[PDB]
Length: 54
DNA sequence: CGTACGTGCGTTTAAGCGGTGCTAGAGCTGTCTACGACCAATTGAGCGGCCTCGGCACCGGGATTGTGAAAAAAAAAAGCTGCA
Ligand SMILES: [Ca+2]
Ligand SMILES: [Ca+2]
Ligand SMILES: [Ca+2]
Ligand SMILES: [Cl-]
Image (cartoon, rainbow, N blue to C red; front, side):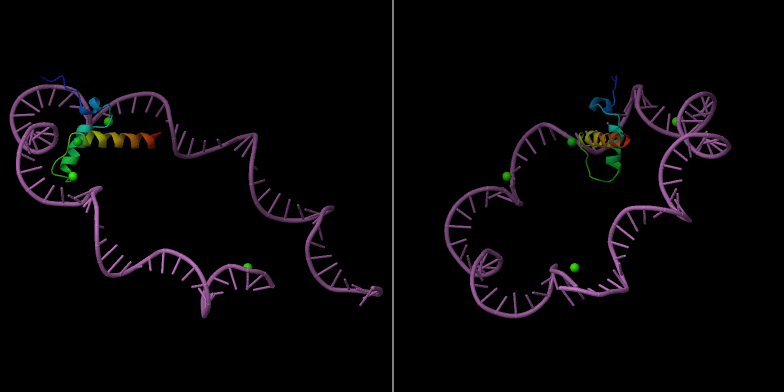
């Protein structure tokens, strides 16, 4: 059991896929959230952040 | 003061209409399982709290840049002439 690594690390991301998945669930957007959606969204928020900081 | 626009004609154009004919594809039904919710147990990422030391705010001094006044030139401008 375990030897757990974060969804962020699996997707090659700094931004928290897991936090993003929980905010989509609790943010009243849809009944269900596919497993790709928070990876994609976390990626987009990382890219945009990187661009503004550059 | 100069001419770009508005009006009003005659000539030309293609929108609109009503109709027909063809089928792409919108959208519906039924089936089945891949995927996401839910759960319980596990644990490590990220939280607040705390301490430090180097960036940056602020200062004074000096270098630098830009502005405005006055004087003097360059130039357009204006009023003034006789001719033609
Ligand atoms: Ca004019
Ligand atoms: Ca179809
Ligand atoms: Ca902190
Ligand atoms: Cl998905």
